[PDB]
Image (tube, rainbow over all chains, first blue to last red; front, side):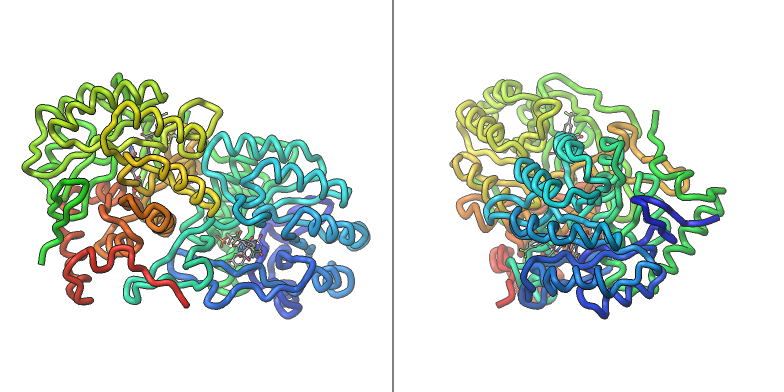
Length: 313
Length: 313
Ligand SMILES: Cc1cc2nc3c(=O)[nH]c(=O)nc-3n(C[C@H](O)[C@H](O)[C@H](O)COP(=O)(O)O)c2cc1C
Ligand SMILES: Cc1cc2nc3c(=O)[nH]c(=O)nc-3n(C[C@H](O)[C@H](O)[C@H](O)COP(=O)(O)O)c2cc1C
Ligand SMILES: O=C(O)c1[nH]c(=O)[nH]c(=O)c1CCc1cc(C(F)(F)F)cc(C(F)(F)F)c1
Ligand SMILES: O=C(O)c1[nH]c(=O)[nH]c(=O)c1CCc1cc(C(F)(F)F)cc(C(F)(F)F)c1
């Protein structure tokens, strides 16, 4: 009985990793994830230039999850690249590196430089399609022509297998369109569903106040609020992209949530909010929990039940 | 201290009403809702001809909320028009009538016939914009050209004040676009935010099966999963549509949740999943809980805090 997986020409002890943004910003964070029993890790979505991000408070958590309008604080591409090329211990686990450029050109500039390191060290690219592009247009993955543009240019600039981080969709025609677009691009080998549930609003009753300062309180939603949404997207893309891997991300607190993500068709399982709340010891719990569920049902590998959610008639 | 208010030229004993779809399909249901403490009620969204809906199971509820893909079962517009026309006791409370036709023409044909009875009795139209039109194109409120067309044609055709039921949005540019559209129409006097969080997927771990039979298990989300989404929407529309009312719908299980909806800017507060689960007694508890929070804070009227949510700095 075991959690092991081989995919994208890498070997993974288990299907768990941090989500981009959580416990992956600094060198201290990355060594922490690396020393965790996570099966992998992903570095904070980066821009060309270092970024302070937005004013605090900017993340908050509650029993049902979290809200965030961080404003993409990061140490800049040169730092994550250097982590990839010189600091990371690949004998421990594989590394994903997440880029989240503010324009198609920023994204092109970075991936061009990422290419040789990817080839030689084996770091794996996650391109973030949630990014805003021009303010007043929707984020890139909610604008299918912009998303088309970004994948042609990045596919061209990088010329290696990469993956993509998708915002959730809520309409069947949107699942169909977005997946048709992704299926145009053979080098996109994996799809991560999902990024935050966009622009919710938490209000505190006692103070009669919103709880995060940027954007009049509006922010992305993670955690228990979003599991079903995350499972629907994982499964929508698992079904429409037969030649790609889907990575699940969305309200994982427990081996049981990891179990459903996988039945839905998840290969890797990312933890954002619950990892922020609990800390990296979460990964041993998630492993034993998923193993406990497997034993009870007589599954010995992940691939016995991956993608095998049943329907009614 | 009482929770009375006046709007759209009607008096309400309190801001509470059922959400469309819940306890409002048959004459039995509507009599029940009328005998309740709700300040108002709304009839099941209706089409010209009666409709069986989708195969069962089609609604499931769990501690954090609900998923549904009912398929718009209803007794057809002749029934609800006749309820509005001959059976409803307007001395008891105001009545809203939801219409949700499958095309603009079906919608035009229902509103013209409704108009006379609205004139005569004061039944209030809630036009449901979270309805698909065409298989393959997104639902109507996710297609701003179609949404403009329904608003144009219905406004022409009905020619009295009416309101619309919106699905949630998740992107700031879509709030701006959506609301710019609704502002084109002076007859739209209320906006109900929000309908279900579209196409989520609940999976059951023990049975490894989705839980509703239609749409491969995919369905609209309500309940605790959607409250911050409903709040962001109420507030986004409240701020962008100053000459309209906003009705809030989404995740109201308590007086507290109702209170956050009003601070977000809601005039009326609708209850779906929580009313499905607890029954119409829920209205007495919600009233008392809200009056209690008001008392403790020294609020005498809803007017005093409606739309008064604080931001930081
Ligand atoms: C504080 C915080 C920062 C995040 N930063 C990023 C980011 O930089 N890039 C990204 O693609 N996703 C980011 N996310 C989204 C997570 O990767 C994840 O998609 C989302 O939180 C849902 O997972 P959860 O439900 O486990 O929180 C962030 C989430 C949080 C809470
Ligand atoms: C069983 C069921 C049937 C519904 N039917 C309708 C409907 O016919 N028309 C409509 O506009 N909304 C319908 N809704 C949506 C609700 O009116 C409400 O927007 C949504 O459930 C979110 O509110 P809640 O969080 O209080 O459930 C339905 C919801 C449920 C759960
Ligand atoms: O840094 C973030 O706000 C963030 N938070 C998430 O939950 N997911 C993300 O992918 C990101 C970073 C991308 C991002 C998102 C946004 C948003 F406000 F549209 F959600 C803004 C920005 C930026 F660059 F503008 F600050 C970046
Ligand atoms: O009766 C519904 O399924 C329903 N459920 C909701 O949560 N909100 C609603 O507004 C409705 C009725 C409108 C509706 C929605 C859908 C859906 F699958 F796009 F959500 C389908 C249909 C229809 F007409 F196809 F049955 C109607």
